[PDB]
Amino acid sequence: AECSVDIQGNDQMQFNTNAITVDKSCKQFTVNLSHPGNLPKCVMGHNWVLSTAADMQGVVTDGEASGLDKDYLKPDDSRVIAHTKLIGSGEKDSVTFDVSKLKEGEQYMFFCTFPGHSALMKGTLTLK
Amino acid sequence: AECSVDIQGNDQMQFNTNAITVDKSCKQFTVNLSHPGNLPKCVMGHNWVLSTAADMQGVVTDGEASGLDKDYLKPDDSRVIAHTKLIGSGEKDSVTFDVSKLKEGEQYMFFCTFPGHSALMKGTLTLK
Ligand SMILES: *C1=CC(=O)N(COCN2C(=O)C=C(*)C2=O)C1=O
Ligand SMILES: [Cu+2]
Ligand SMILES: [Cu+2]
Ligand code: NI
Ligand code: NI
């Protein structure tokens, strides 16, 4: 099975996917984020952050309050299982993490922590 | 009948209303916009813009492309029936327009033209 996925965040504030499935046979999983828009990071910056469904709100609130210089993520936030950098137009970034950090039966959410974006930019991630 | 309405745009990128009814007995209509959030205009700026449902997309595209210095509205856009200024946290602005600019049967939309916000920040306005 494949253990990577390519995701896009555009100017309309949206991911080209709302659900991800991580095959249990994967040892590591990679996410390739790319920004096909024309707006700069400071106004339409997108990052891909993964946490349990329960931790999402907390991560989003503290992240938005941390500012652009911190890529909108409270430093040393242990709730973030994995995440890419905040990218602007024409930029791209990848993250690879150990699938052992995921458990079956648990509910995970991926989302962008740029002020207000998680309202639309979010989706589910499951270990099947 | 009342001829004004108070609207709020917060940090969660949302209006506290999605439908406005302008009573035909009104000669003028006023909209009081206020920003109860803490985020600045440059990151979570909100404006209240009115156009026909059909002109909305056009207005939004040309507006987002106009930048913060223009309050995200293409200069001299004749599609904009009325609008307030773009406001940041703790700011407010009112707009009053002639109800004679509205006709019955026509579908109107109000929305924010800050990059990507119209996806969630929009609503209907009707002359009944
Ligand atoms: C992209 C990065 C950046 O700093 N910037 C300018 O932002 C200016 N302002 C402003 O006027 C109020 C808050 C703020 O960041 C970009 O366009
Ligand atoms: Cu985003
Ligand atoms: Cu807005
Ligand atoms: Ni495989
Ligand atoms: Ni009246």
Image: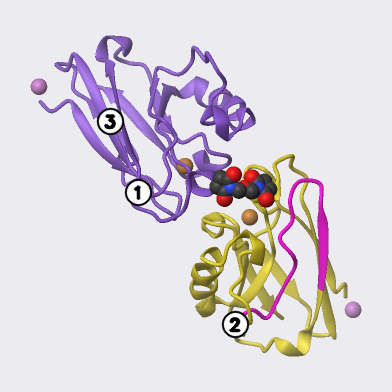
Chain colours: A purple, B yellow
Q: Chain of mark 3?
A: A
Q: Horizontal and vertical percent for residue A19?
A: 31, 36
Disc 2 versus disc 1: nearer the observer: 1
Residue bearing mark 1:
A90
Residue A31 shows which numbered tag? 3
Q: Is residue A55 left or right of residue B68?
A: left
Q: Are marks 3 and 1 in contact (CB under 8 Å)?
A: no
Residue type at the position of mark 3: Val
Spatial CA span between label 3 and label 1: 17 Å
Residue type at the position of mark 1: Gly
Spatial CA span between label 2 and label 3: 42 Å
Ligand 3 is within 8 Å of the C-beta of the residue at disc 2: no
The front one of A88 and B106 is A88
Residue B57 shows which numbered tag? none
Residue bearing mark 2:
B79
Disc 3 versus disc 1: nearer the observer: 1
**Magenta region: which residues?**
B80-95
Residue at x-position 36% and y-position 16%: A106
The front one of B8 and A46 is A46
Residue at x-position 64% and y-position 30%: A65
B128, above or below A115, in the image: below
As helix, strand or loop, the secondary structure at mark 3 comes to: strand
Q: Does the magenta segment cover residue A61?
A: no
